[PDB]
Amino acid sequence: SKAAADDFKEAFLLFDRTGDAKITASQVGDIARALGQNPTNAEINKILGNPSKEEMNAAAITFEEFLPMLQAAANNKDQGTFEDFVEGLRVFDKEGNGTVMGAELRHVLATLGEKMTEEEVEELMKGQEDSNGCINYEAFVKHIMSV
Amino acid sequence: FDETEIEDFKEAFTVIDQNADGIIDKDDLRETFAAMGRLNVKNEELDAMIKEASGPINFTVFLTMFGEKLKGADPEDVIMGAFKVLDPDGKGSIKKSFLEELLTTGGGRFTPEEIKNMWAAFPPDVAGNVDYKNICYVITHGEDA
Amino acid sequence: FDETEIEDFKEAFTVIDQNADGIIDKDDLRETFAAMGRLNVKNEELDAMIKEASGPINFTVFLTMFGEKLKGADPEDVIMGAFKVLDPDGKGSIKKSFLEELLTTGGGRFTPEEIKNMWAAFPPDVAGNVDYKNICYVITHGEDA
Image 1 (cartoon, helix red, strand yellow):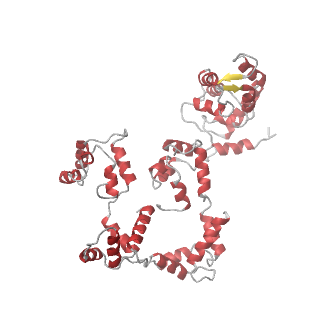
Image 2 (cartoon, rainbow over the protein chains, first blue to last red):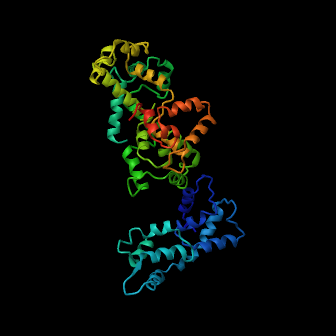
Image 3 (cartoon, each protein chain N blue to C red):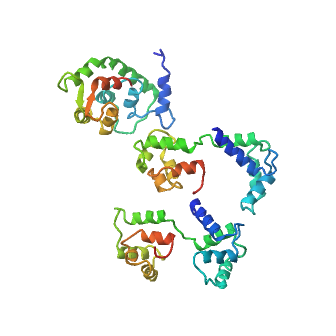
């Protein structure tokens, strides 16, 4: 709205590697996340196809399509409730203390639903899981929502 | 410009200014080259060095000319800082394809063609991204060591 | 000529120039040979070394004489680079007949007769093309190790 945030246009100049002021359709998922929006990858996929837009063939972009796609994704930020994130992992391990065994969270984050690479899974556990093999998800989900 | 790097350019300015008056003229350039072994140094090379300045080469004109050519010059300790962050487990030289992908995919300065020129005199290990450290040496002091 | 190879020739020039004035004369040649154990070094050997130069042996005359005799000299890391491309799976020394066929059939410098001379002091393994690495050693520093 501007509140006209012109820093979204300045961040588009940091993600366009050619400097022509266009951003390919394959970058739009990760740049919506870097502007403070977490649409799921199936949602980013649907919307695209919904608009008869094929992410399979070469793509370019213009700021005039990327701005309204970020504004259509911005209504879905009401789905980001931290009660359900901590209660999900609280149902994932027994006893009254928030600890996932290391390999349980790593294999679930790579193979269940939207596949996260094991390189990204190791980069998200690095520091929050110590050598006991127990990830405290009270501080883990706190630090994941700090970015 | 750190102060020890400016003192290194002051010492190089004094070794090329053999009249010790504070201004490197064309005779100082020719007599420094003749003392390094250049008996055939042409006057057109000395004139092309003086044609890069708008005035006489005193210490601040030599510093501003080197500043404007070395606008991305990085000392060896900060290049090894960045390469220790690229190899955060220490000791190992990083893979060839990892440096090619991370140069391109992060920045436009890391585009490929430029990556072929990086491999081209910065040899294999250096080019590949496996060794490390020899490239920091030759970026602060050129030519083969 | 890489710069560390030129620094190795500067250190060898300083060990043969025992007067430390920058020019290796015939007395320096004889006193370096006597300090290595050559008590019978003839004056005709010293005169044949000086007969390869047109002037006094200063550092740039010694570098140009070694440059003109070593116009295909290759450092050990680039010889092992080429032998790792000939054995691209690593570790194994390559077969005798594979190096004889690939030397001949690619280039005229790899003709056979020359391949018999390669096997002749570069022993079997080396000659054969099975070992590897000892030949890179003796091409950068001669004689049996």
